[PDB]
Image: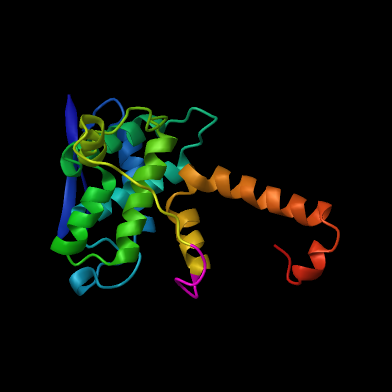
Amino acid sequence: STRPLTLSHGSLEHVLLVPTASFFIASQLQEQFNKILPEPTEGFAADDEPTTPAELVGKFLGYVSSLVEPSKVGQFDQVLNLCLTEFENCYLEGNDIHALAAKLLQENDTTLVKTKELIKNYITARIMAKRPFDKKSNSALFRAVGEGNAQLVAIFGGQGNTDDYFEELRDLYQTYHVLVGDLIKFSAETLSELIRTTLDAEKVFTQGL
């Protein structure tokens, strides 16, 4: 037994068949999320408000994932897993979150920042819901490599491609915190230690690292 829960923002909406056993806590989160969400506008052109039902369910996923603690089992965990499963079956037709994001970019009037926010919400939710990416993907490219239909070479850039390289690291830290946060903390600690243990390195790092 389930009851429909409507989460909406102006014209666009999504209905979620919540189990009656956890509908009480889902209605709580619905009320909290609807309070957090900004006021609807024409064309959804303003920032931090969804343009498509996919974005809106993303933001709701995002909000619930913010409250759920990874260490401590909470009441919101079951609602997270439930609305995650709904998002997957409704918008990820077996495909990857990037494939969806890329679909939205060319079809709907979604901006690049809104799209990255959607990816971050989905990926954060996946990790908070104790559902890592342990299953190997069915990516066509890597399927083709296994079968011997494709040969892959990786190339790494260097200096002089962009003047604002640091915003690329900023975007990685924002969007993929739950995937690379530990790499960036490790790399930051390694560099701090190399400055400390290298004789005159601090002289070269005038505003620190």
**Image height of 50 relative to 5, above or below:** below
Report if residue 38 is visible in the image: no
**Image height of 168 relative to 60, above or below:** below
In the picture, which quadrant includes the C terminus?
bottom right
Is residue 163 magenta-colored?
yes
Q: Position of residue 205 (x, y in %)?
A: 74, 68
Front residue of 107/32: it is 107
Front residue of 112/87: it is 112
Q: Residue at x 34, y 69 (%)?
A: 47
Image quadrant where residue 161 sits: bottom left
Which span of residues is magenta-colored?
Answer: 158-164
**Image height of 101 relative to 106, above or below:** above
Q: Is residue 89 left or right of residue 39?
A: left
Is residue 175 magenta-colored?
no
In the picture, which quadrant includes the N terminus?
top left
Q: Position of residue 150 (x, y in %)?
A: 23, 41
Q: Residue at x 46, y 63 (%)?
A: 168
Q: Position of residue 127 (x, y in %)?
A: 42, 36
